[PDB]
Amino acid sequence: TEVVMENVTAFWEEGGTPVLKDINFKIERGQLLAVAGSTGAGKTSLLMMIMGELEPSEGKIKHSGRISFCSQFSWIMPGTIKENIIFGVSYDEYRYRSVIKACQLEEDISKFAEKDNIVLGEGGITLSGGQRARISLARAVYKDADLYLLDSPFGYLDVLTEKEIFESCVCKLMANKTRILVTSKMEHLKKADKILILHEGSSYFYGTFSELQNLQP
Ligand SMILES: Nc1nc2c(ncn2[C@H]2C[C@H](O)[C@@H](COP(=O)(O)OP(=O)(O)OP(=O)(O)O)O2)c(=O)[nH]1
Ligand SMILES: [Mg+2]
């Protein structure tokens, strides 16, 4: 197993209300877990526990190896689009190009005279929200890691573009990698190896899309 939570309860503030309550899941190496639920359910907090910024008050957590995290808030630092995606990692043309293509950024980049050397975050180009989200996702996916934590990475994208990048990047390009994707979309839950639906900190549902279908619903 690559990631396990067993009976996990946690608090952001000592003596407050628990942000996660008796959470249970297991991800094997190379699987995809979809984490769903309404605002404030605790999805980002769950990711924060995996990254060690929130310790459990009850229960056990297992995870090993380096993590690549994609925030639900897209961000850019001053530098070229290539520098923003590589972001200090060693450069490889094939790897970079595969990520760019999987994130539909090659069409964006091909339109600039400076191509991948277009400068962002310095007052020149002002990117759309969808462009910033895909750059942020590409940055997280380019990093080599054992576990990818993708927190609602499809912000500002229309539903078809989201579907295409979910398939090309999360399912195809990242097929061999252990992935936790915070997402609410039906196809993502259907393609995930496991689904965890959170509601106000608790496990609303945990299992497979097929199991949920068999309950009616
Ligand atoms: N005291 C404190 N509470 C936090 C913090 N971060 C989140 N919370 C609270 C707010 C919520 O009541 C609860 C869950 O917040 P989350 O950000 O984990 O929710 P989630 O990511 O599911 O919501 P989202 O879809 O991103 O709007 O925890 C924090 O850093 N400090
Ligand atoms: Mg969140």
Image (cartoon, grey):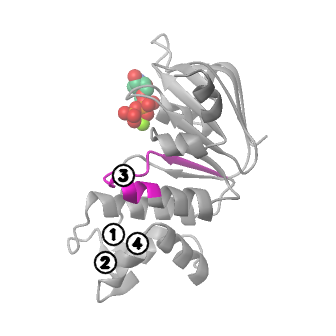
Task: Please state which of the two labelled residues, at mark 3 or mark 1, is closer to the viewer.
Answer: 3
Mark 1 residue element: loop
Q: Which of marks 2 and 3 is nearer the N terminus?
A: 2
Where residue 5 sits: x, y (%)?
Answer: 69, 28
Distance in Å between CA atoms under marks 2 and 4: 15 Å
Tell me the distance, in whole angstroms, between the alpha carbons under discs 4 and 3. 17 Å
Magenta region: which residues?
147-163
Could you classify mark 1 by the number of other residues whose Cα lies within 10 Å: few (under 14), some (14-19), or many (20 or more)? Answer: few
Q: Name the residue under label 1.
A: 78
Mark nearest the camera among 2 and 4 is 4
Q: In this view, does 199 lie to the left or right of 148?
A: left
Residue displayed at 55% across by 32% down:
46
Q: Name the residue under label 4.
A: 105
Q: Which mark is residue 119?
A: 2
Above-or-below relation of 191 to 116: above
> Up-down: is 95 above or below 129?
below
Question: Do the numbered discs 2 and 1 sit on residues whose CB atoms are within 8 Å?
Answer: yes
Horizontal side, residue 172 vs residue 116: left or right: right
